[PDB]
Length: 317
Length: 320
Ligand SMILES: Cc1cc2nc3c(=O)[nH]c(=O)nc-3n(C[C@H](O)[C@H](O)[C@H](O)COP(=O)(O)O)c2cc1C
Ligand SMILES: Cc1cc2nc3c(=O)[nH]c(=O)nc-3n(C[C@H](O)[C@H](O)[C@H](O)COP(=O)(O)O)c2cc1C
Ligand SMILES: [Cl-]
Ligand SMILES: [Cl-]
Ligand SMILES: [Cl-]
Ligand SMILES: [Cl-]
Ligand SMILES: [Cl-]
Ligand SMILES: [Mg+2]
Image (cartoon, rainbow over all chains, first blue to last red; front, side):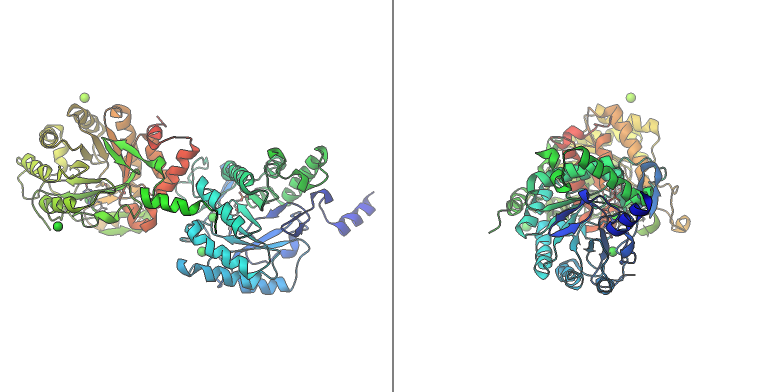
């Protein structure tokens, strides 16, 4: 009955409790969060929960301040921006002044002007400035528009970065990886993440490949990462490899081409503890998150699952 | 106390070289550890032979070099170049000394062209002399009859003039001999040149040199930057359609090497799959730097695994 229901919804929030879980020590009310690069400076922090996201990842943000084509035939996007943002310090100040009702992850990346060999201390400083307030921290070493950044995923470079971030804060630390890594790179990053006692891995960032695109005149468009369904196959493949290798030892967050509740359920069942999307929200609207979540809740209830956690990785056991 | 595998992969790369073994192939009896090479014109005199593997290349083609010694605009909107220089080089004799001093590592091809002074009714004996000198030390030799800045050179592509050059050179050495062609050739000449190469049992064809065309250019004011060959992305369309034509017609009989406008891993996979056994690049290295080649190789490896190609050779020509 509506007057009551309106009070229940207002009081408890918009997602079914069955969706709630703890991941790396953090209570997430629902598994689909907003991926990085949308709320770059944390200017809509209080809106995300009312829009039916379980959490939001803010950034990428950099140690210093540094103040997009629709591909509709592919239901995809091509991103031409680097890390435009007001810096990690500015974000910390915003976060201190609250502190939304859902978890806020912070995504940190190397300031553009920082030389590669000074990358370690640039990540360290961002982590130090925002880590206390963030629910979790993600080291972005995978965005293609920042020159040289993907090179830091080689384990010889990555280790000192991840080690410095992880020693700086007891906030959970994750790493965000590219979709195009070799199998042996994926295995090695996975093992490094376990070895450094990180909380998890976010897979995947955008791809630079334009293979498969229908949208006409895509040739003409310049450099930039590709998002959306072009990533979906790889992102699931990468998820299943990591889950099989290291899924008992850290959490996996799956991102890349999630459009429908079916997409999302396949990721959970394949070993994703949490999800994100960016592209499908742009093509899909406010509904979008809220419809995906009702879809997951239905599949948990219909399957025998007393909780989300119980479903995670359930197709691989 | 790490139980990681990465330290052992580091040793593997140290012992075996940086490239994924899947990228390795044999083409005209030479083992190329990876398919993207440095195109001619950049290391003219074999001055950085030991450095090219380290840049990520699978091989390098050095020259053009001529029998006797004879010692560019950035088109930024097209990520292209306009070259106005001819064949400045220290000559085949000097290069042979460097080749003989080089401790192996990746194959080194040598690109030979006619000495500018040399008549043309005397081109044969010039090409022969160079072949004699660098032939014995090169992994392969290419006969360049396609560079635009050398007066009268592209005329040599006429089968009637090309025949005795390729034939004298092929007869001088047992080193695989290839021919490098211009993109501006008519399709009928392309078929006859391909047929000649097969007729003379050549090892392959390198396609393409630079273009004289000015069509397709985005950079303002090219129209009075003056004469010269254009390289980079503007060649890509013609380079791919020459590659497909040649592979369709003559791809069983000799190797095709694709060059012209390869920028990305996507570009490179497309060439492979259209029938290039090997690739080269110049412009893309100028723009994309020390990384560029290494990036193309890791993308080919990923697509071979994907795949699931057991070796590079299996994918060459898979699109056709
Ligand atoms: C326009 C745009 C900007 C992005 N900016 C960032 C960023 O700053 N940091 C980051 O880690 N990922 C960034 N991403 C990647 C997304 O966070 C996400 O990993 C990717 O788009 C795959 O998800 P999707 O297919 O649901 O879009 C961006 C993506 C898009 C489309
Ligand atoms: C500055 C410059 C010098 C070159 N010199 C030679 C040469 O001496 N001999 C040759 O066969 N090709 C030469 N080339 C042609 C390249 O080997 C290549 O065929 C052409 O540039 C297309 O490839 P790219 O688009 O990757 O540069 C030269 C190209 C450039 C840009
Ligand atoms: Cl940037
Ligand atoms: Cl991107
Ligand atoms: Cl000349
Ligand atoms: Cl000596
Ligand atoms: Cl030229
Ligand atoms: Mg014929």
